[PDB]
Image 1 (tube, chains in turn blue, yellow):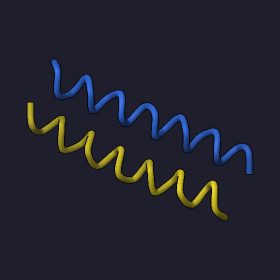
Image 2 (image 1 turned 90 degrees about the vertical axis):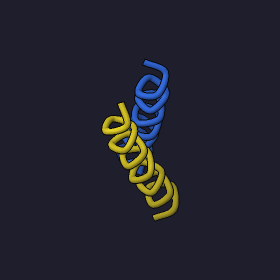
Image 3 (image 1 turned 180 degrees about the horizontal axis):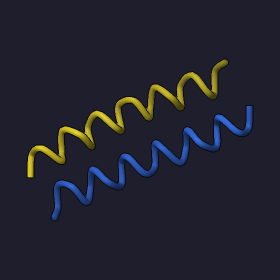
Image 4 (image 1 turned 90 degrees about the horizontal axis):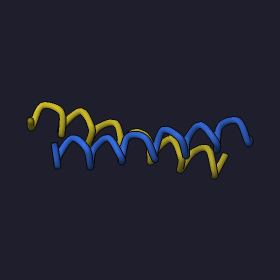
Length: 25
Length: 25
């Protein structure tokens, strides 16, 4: 349960921050 | 420019789906 939630957060945070970086630069 | 936005939009979209499922089931 932890292993999936943690990874999900990581993937969510990553993909979003990438989007920010993708647009701005 | 937009090519990377699309990939990022998709990555985040799947990632939030991943977080939804992980927290739920």
